[PDB]
Length: 387
Ligand SMILES: [Br-]
Ligand SMILES: [Cl-]
Ligand SMILES: [Cl-]
Ligand SMILES: [Cl-]
Ligand SMILES: [Cl-]
Ligand SMILES: [K+]
Image (tube, rainbow, N blue to C red):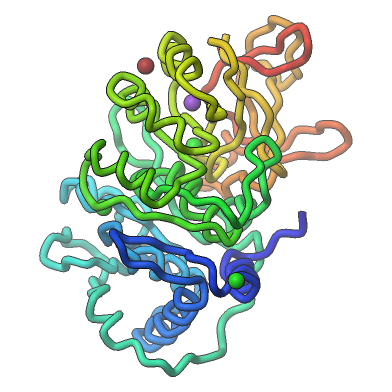
């Protein structure tokens, strides 16, 4: 429960599991030792290319081993990464970079980037200049230092910048009791990198010694995904509601190859969960995530199909408060508030942060909560349910 910055956890994990497979792309496999060496070589290049701690650096790199190498190397030098979907239109990309205050954009295709205040660097040319020579003077990083910026948005899709601390994703190295996950597991990287949900896949894998098999770039091809799940022995499968429901409709057997399936997003129609759970013995979970809590935040194990939020992940606390910030009684409707290691550092404007990140005395601690938009209450057993 003493959390470190991501590069420090990864250093420990890679030293402890150097021979385990960290990344799979098509049929290419990269051990933790190989990945660690490439991250170190690239971090030295990034220091050579005038990046420093605190720099806001966007990443626009298609799914590939290099994408994750850049994530690790940027965090090692203390940069704040801003991952961008490669399929996003140029205007929304400019909107994201402007919202984030990005100063640099690292891309695997510099010809498809919007013009703005940022400086564009070529990921492929940077990789090309990597030497075996590792370097050495990296910044001291706290679990509370910024690591990442994700966007959230309302009805109109205008992006709002969310600053994520190292601890917010470093917590994903803590094994989740309901999942039973460990270094023996394999995850599938398919969520878009600009989504908090992508952190579930990347960091639960790489901060535990487990394997991350990387989906091909582009929109999902369920035949290729089904082959990938089987061929690469995916054991922890995170799916959006849409991808989950579509697999139920067209290939439900694929869902029972893994040990655990976690469904993120707005609740899928329970009839579809009913079909899925009747079709095999995989443990199927409804997951609750929140961009302002960095990643997946709670899990409810669906055995039969309001919506229970289930059991929070390690170092996550959840409470339902009403409009006057009082803990709700049974059946009283309020909002879900989330506290703990995942809570974002805030938004880019501090007046926006002050109204949604609220300190409330709870069970003896003056605890910082994020106020979600999720309406909720308590059931008769003091379990949180969404309404
Ligand atoms: Br649905
Ligand atoms: Cl090993
Ligand atoms: Cl903002
Ligand atoms: Cl991609
Ligand atoms: Cl999530
Ligand atoms: K969900």
